[PDB]
Structures are given as structure tokens and as C-alpha cells.
Length: 267
Ligand SMILES: CC(=O)N[C@H]1[C@H](O[C@H]2[C@@H](O)[C@@H](CO)O[C@H](O[C@@H]3[C@H](O)[C@@H](O)[C@H](O[C@H]4[C@H](O)[C@@H](O)[C@H](O)O[C@@H]4CO)O[C@@H]3CO)[C@@H]2O)O[C@H](CO)[C@H](O)[C@@H]1O[C@@H]1O[C@H](CO)[C@H](O)[C@H](O)[C@H]1O
Ligand SMILES: *[C@@H]1O[C@H](CO[C@@H]2O[C@@H](C)[C@@H](O)[C@@H](O)[C@@H]2O)[C@@H](O[C@@H]2O[C@H](CO)[C@@H](O)[C@H](O)[C@H]2NC(C)=O)[C@H](O)[C@H]1NC(C)=O
Ligand SMILES: *[C@@H]1O[C@H](CO)[C@@H](O[C@@H]2O[C@H](CO)[C@@H](O)[C@H](O)[C@H]2NC(C)=O)[C@H](O)[C@H]1NC(C)=O
Ligand SMILES: O=c1ccn([C@@H]2O[C@H](COP(=O)(O)OP(=O)(O)O)[C@@H](O)[C@H]2O)c(=O)[nH]1
Ligand SMILES: [Mn+2]
Image 1 (cartoon, helix red, strand yellow):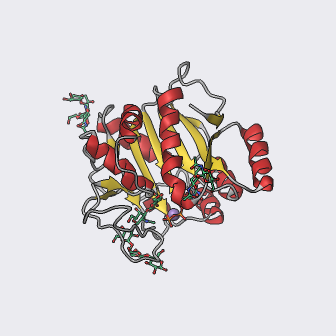
Image 2 (cartoon, rainbow, N blue to C red; image 1 turned 45 degrees about the vertical axis):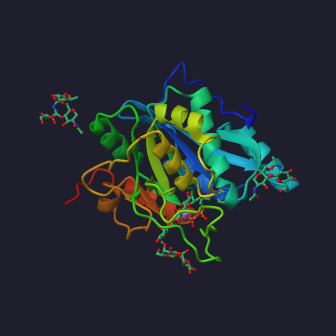
């Protein structure tokens, strides 16, 4: 498939229950280490396997290239292809991850694409997924259903009319973190080259899902994905899946808080 780095894993032998694909730039080693030490640590969750991989492109910086080569060798959990790893190539990055699931891990029951400035509660997510009774054509997250493209020309998420010429975006889920059954990867990969390209990855996946007639659904009767962030508390964070706006030091402190308070009951 044209990959420069492949994780040392065999999904055929031991099909994972949940695969996390984490986006981060080359310089964000601190993010990746914090994740590896917290919600990214591979383990059995209620007897289900969790696997965690980091998606990277390439960079022009020789120093960063060497750093990442060393990191891959040391940890063996990086998925890499030869594309310039910049914000406006995130669509390529996401498609790389999806391509990977399709080629080397179609046995994954579920896949979460997530960002690195995130807190993820894998235990509660696994509980809600096992409760959902859905194993195919399943896609959930924070649903963004009547979105309009941002036309402010200097905005981080600006798209011109030539980049995206219609008044509304398809239904899609926030790219801060979304979850889908493993089969969905193959479908999206198959259809991706025939769907109009857009440089916003979560929107592009929404376009693919729309072409596939895959409907978005809420994971639970209460909201569980929070792209806007949250005021922290142990009891709240025990009953959410994903929270945005979390820098590495904060992630480590929050993980510590959950460990320090394990075994206490919550209202
Ligand atoms: C982080 C996030 O959720 N970003 C996604 C973005 O969300 C925004 C949209 O839904 C718009 C639509 O109304 O509302 C929200 O933001 C509005 C406004 O549009 C923003 O411009 C503004 O934020 C800026 C402000 O404009 C600046 O002046 C100021 O300096 O900074 C602030 C914050 O940076 O805020 C208001 C209220 O928050 C909402 O945040 O929607 C995008 C598509 O249009 C994307 O979905 C984007 O998500 C990221 O997209 C990339 C695409 O490659 C990846 O999927 C990332 O993983 C994903 O996080
Ligand atoms: C998911 O299913 C569970 C289990 O229910 C069984 O399997 C399902 C696929 C469906 O065919 C059910 O009719 C089966 O009974 C559901 O949780 C059950 O609900 C019962 C009664 O409401 C309750 O005692 C327990 O919660 C569960 N019982 C058993 C036998 O497991 C659950 O509601 C289903 N979830 C969704 C999202 O539909
Ligand atoms: C996304 O990545 C691609 C692949 O690296 C970039 O395309 C290359 O860009 C370099 C210069 O930046 C050229 O020398 C290559 O010829 C290009 N190759 C291909 C296959 O396109 C692309 O520029 C990146 N996108 C953005 C917005 O930076
Ligand atoms: O060149 C880049 C820029 C960003 N990102 C990742 O893409 C996600 C979105 O970045 P950011 O939080 O800046 O986007 P925002 O949520 O503010 O839209 C994050 O996990 C970044 O680490 C990446 O992999 N490569
Ligand atoms: Mn972010």
C-alpha cells in the first residue's frame, strides 16, 4: 500500500476489539508519550483488546525525520506514508489510517480516529459499544448535522467556493474523535477516490459515508463526545468518551486523578 512504517502487530492472529488511530505532527512527541502513558496504553478492557497507533506523514526537517525513525524503532506503533504532514493534508493522514485498517487489520471490531489534544475514556467507550449491539455500518461521535462551510478567508477552517462549492456540509462527526465499526474502513477506502476531495478530514469522511448510505447515530442517550471541552471532575470524566482541549500535562494530571480516585463511588 506504499507504507514507510507498519506497526509490529498481527490482527489476524488476535483481532483487536478497539483500534485507536491518533493524529499528531512530527514535533508533538510529548503528546504521543502522554497518550502512550495514559489512555493509549494497550491492555485488555473487560477482556477486549485495545491497540493504539500513531499516524504520521513525512517532513522536510532531517532532524524530525531521524527523531521519528528512532521513535518508531523504539515503540513500533507508528503508521507512516510519504506525504507532507501539514494541517491541510489531514485528509491524507486520515485516509492513511483507514487504508491501514483495510489492508492490515480488517478484523478490528471498532476503530476510533482521534486527535492528540484529547482525553479518551476507553473503558466507558468499550462499555457503550458492547451495549450498542452494532457490528457493521456503524459510525458515531459528536454529530455535526447542519454545518455550513466557513467562508471567513483567514479562518483555520476556511474553504473557498472552489474548494467546496455548496451551501451545507454533509452530516459528519467532529474530527476530534469519532468511532466506526471496522468494516466501515474498507467501504470508505473503496469509495474515497470517487468522492469530491476536501481538505477537512472529518467532512471528507462524512462525504464518503453519505455516498455509502451509512447513517450517523448517537453512541448513547447522553452526550459522550465533547469537542468544546469540559470542566474536569472525576465523576464526570468517568461517564464520557472523549474530551477536547487537553494538553499533555493536563492529560497526565487527569489520568493521575482517575487513578488516585479509583475505587470511590460517584453520585
Ligand atoms: C476544534 C473543532 O471542533 N473544529 C472544527 C470546526 O468546528 C467549528 C464549526 O463547527 C463552526 C461552525 O459554526 O462552529 C464552531 O466554531 C465557531 C467559529 O466557526 C470558529 O471560527 C470560532 O473559532 C475561532 C475564531 O473564529 C477565531 O477568531 C479565534 O481566534 O479562534 C477561535 C478558536 O480557534 O469559534 C466558533 C465557536 O467555537 C466550531 O468550533 O469545524 C470545522 C469544519 O468547518 C472542522 O470540523 C473542525 O474540526 C477539525 O477539522 C480538521 C479537518 O482536517 C480535523 O478533522 C480535526 O481533527 C478537527 O478537530
Ligand atoms: C442489546 O441486546 C441486549 C441483550 O438482549 C438480547 O439480545 C439482543 C440482540 C436482542 O435480540 C434482545 O431481544 C435479546 O434479549 C439488550 O439488553 C437486554 O435487555 C434486557 C431486557 O430489556 C435486560 O434484562 C438486559 O439489559 C439485557 N438482557 C440480556 C438477556 O442480555 C440491550 O437492550 C440491547 N441494546 C440495544 C442498544 O438495543
Ligand atoms: C500534501 O502532501 C503532498 C505529498 O507530500 C504534497 O505534494 C508534494 O509537494 C511537494 C512540495 O511541498 C512537491 O515537491 C511534490 O511534487 C508534491 N507531490 C505530490 C505527489 O503532490 C502536498 O503539497 C501537500 N499538501 C499541502 C497543502 O501541503
Ligand atoms: O501538521 C499537522 C497538524 C495537526 N495535526 C494533528 O491534527 C489534529 C488537529 O489539530 P488541531 O488541534 O490544531 O486542530 P483544531 O482541533 O484546533 O481544529 C491534532 O491531533 C494535531 O496534532 C497533525 O497530525 N499534523
Ligand atoms: Mn484540536
